[PDB]
Amino acid sequence: PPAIREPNAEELQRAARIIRHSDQPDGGLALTGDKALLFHESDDAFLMYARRGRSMIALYDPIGPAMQRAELIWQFRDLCDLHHARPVFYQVRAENLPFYMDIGLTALKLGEEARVDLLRFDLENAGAAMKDLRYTWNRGQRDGLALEFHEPGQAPLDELKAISDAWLEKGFSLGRFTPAYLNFFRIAIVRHQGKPVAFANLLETDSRELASLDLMRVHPDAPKLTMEFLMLGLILHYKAQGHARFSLGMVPLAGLQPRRGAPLTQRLGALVFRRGEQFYNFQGLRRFKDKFQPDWEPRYLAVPAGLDPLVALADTAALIA
Ligand SMILES: [Ca+2]
Ligand SMILES: [Cl-]
Ligand SMILES: [Cl-]
Ligand code: NA
């Protein structure tokens, strides 16, 4: 069986086209080039994945139309069997579980994704959360914070490096601070009285269903408000652009409201994020995202049914680390 390999420049351009035509901006993670790409037999869909131990671990649901996603999942099962490897899907949506169920996988809760409904979102709405946001926006501007947007390839790289350096690659589920990769994206920069203090690359598609985040890095010496200001600014930006939803990203299990007495399928997923003698607890991450009144949806780890998931969990942990 032919060797699993990283994509070439041409394959990446094909992925990019597919992402643009999709409603799944998070497919942009493919563009780092550190994940193998499995293309649907029409180049209208793709699945991205990496190998760790005897697991082949896909990142997210496949990118593309519904039928092609379902077909790529069966393809991937075949491909894993061909390589004597177990299939694993990292961070997938509930609506696709029946497809994973059909290729013989069960699922473990991994965490929850926060998405803002941009249509219903409004700073003048009732409640304390909006009041606090209105304060952040005004105070922020009063204090010399300003958000700017750059078309792909136009952000001043060397000013980004400064920020990125102070704030510090894990890969797979994360973007890479490289020109090659960042050149694919619109980039937002927060300046404090002219000085760059945070940035974020923006994951979009040609449609306005969904925009989301990849790298978001703030200077350690930036004003405390900087990260909230940036996020609020992005939400306001995409609301104004006519986008429907904006994704704030996932909070893993241990960062959610605790649930002892919960069955193991809703607990074992924490094993993906261990830090020495301790689980990553992601303190405050959930609280921060909740500032924007998102909606929350579970994300799952799909793993072989009937078999002890510890080994798939170990492989996923190594991959994510
Ligand atoms: Ca299996
Ligand atoms: Cl007010
Ligand atoms: Cl546009
Ligand atoms: Na088809």
Image (spheres, rainbow, N blue to C red):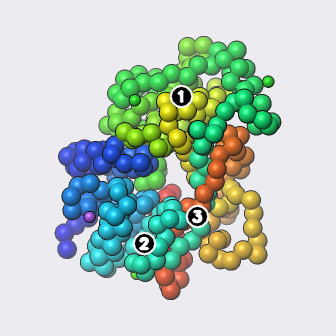
Instruction: Tell me if 46 is positioned left or right of 25 in this view.
Output: left
Quick one: SS at disc 2?
Answer: helix
- Nearest the eye: 264 or 134: 134
Discs 3, 1 touching: Cβ within 8 Å: no
Residue 110, disc: 3
Classify the position of the N terminus by image quarter: bottom left
Q: Residues within 10 Å of mark 3 (few under 14, many from 20)?
A: many
Question: Is the CB atom of the residue marked by disc 2 within 8 angstroms of ligand 4's nearest atom?
Answer: no
Q: Earlier in the sequence, mark 3 or mark 1?
A: 3
Q: Position of residue 217 (x, y in %)?
A: 55, 35
The residue that label 2 is drawn on is: 99
Question: Is the CB atom of the residue marked by disc 1 within 8 angstroms of ligand 3's nearest atom?
Answer: no
Q: Earlier in the sequence, mark 1 or mark 2?
A: 2
- Nearest the eye: 117 or 26: 117
The residue that label 1 is drawn on is: 240
Quick one: SS at disc 3?
Answer: strand
Residue at 60% of width from left, 57% of height from top?
Answer: 297
Whole-number angstrom distance, CA of label 1 to CA of label 2:
36 Å
User: Which residue type does callout 1 highlight?
Assistant: Ala
Whole-number angstrom distance, CA of label 3 to CA of label 1:
32 Å
Q: Position of residue 247 (x, y in %)?
A: 55, 45
Q: Earlier in the sequence, mark 2 or mark 3?
A: 2
Instruction: Tell me if 312 is positioned left or right of 281 in this view.
Output: left
